[PDB]
Length: 54
Length: 108
View 1: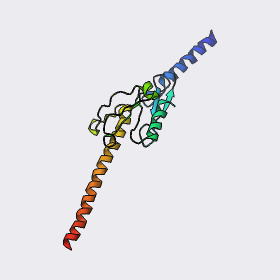
View 2 (view 1 turned 30 degrees about the vertical axis):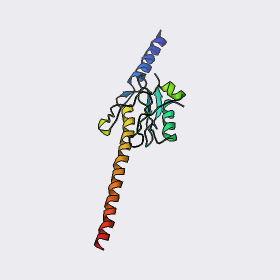
View 3 (view 1 turned 90 degrees about the horizontal axis):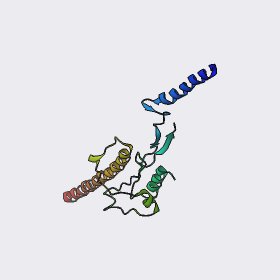
């Protein structure tokens, strides 16, 4: 029981880490980020997609 | 190739049309009026998979960047605009130079 209680606490910690991490306002690990393309060139259609998973 | 790489490939192989990818993942081909004079007939296996739609008109006055797709398309529109602007300047440049030479001859 004692260990499980500790695991349960750590468990919640992982969950918050995933739901609290936020570059500025945009969340990252919650799962909403999905995939965004980052234009890294001086012309359109140069963006390279980047994906963050739950 | 992923949708984004496809767009870059097109932009690389041709300068007649300028591709882009919106937020959902749809491809955005823009053809400036100063280069193309009519609707483009997209064809081929890729076309079949992409199912390219009609060509709405997009003048600078209509550039909305509140969405990535709109931003990407807007870059293309601005580029077509800059070309039109410059070209006109060039034309006017000749006028000045031509009138300059004319003044010289008239004075002679």
